[PDB]
Length: 54
Length: 69
Image (cartoon, rainbow over all chains, first blue to last red; front, side, top):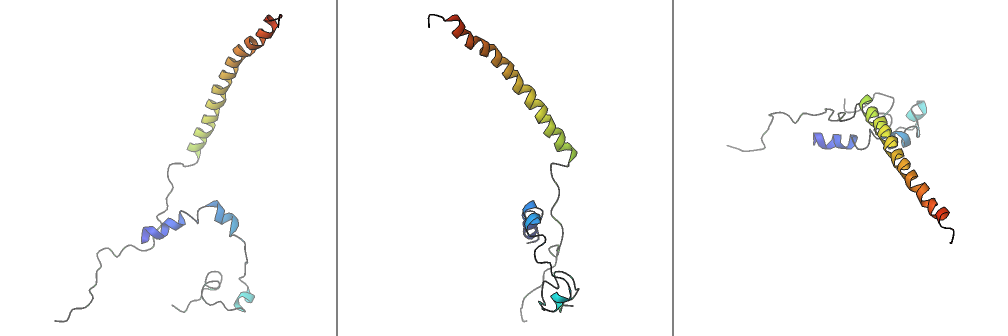
């Protein structure tokens, strides 16, 4: 599986297409993002270093 | 004796490692081939255009040579 997951990165992440499109869409990281409460990802994905796992 | 599920270690699969690595082209090397193909490209193309001139004058000569037409 270790090689299989990194095959997606060589296909999607390094490409110009994703770095042109998905970059700068719905940038929400402020106290307002905390005022919506997404819990998993979003806040975890960007900003606050918080998780229930730890 | 009671038998259940057994554990296996050996190498532990090796989790989280960058498999992505740069191959073939480096940067400066591909530009030498790129401009090199261009320099070979224009030089070989214009030689046929000079060879076309041998035909070009000779083809239009047929109209000048033929006046009973």
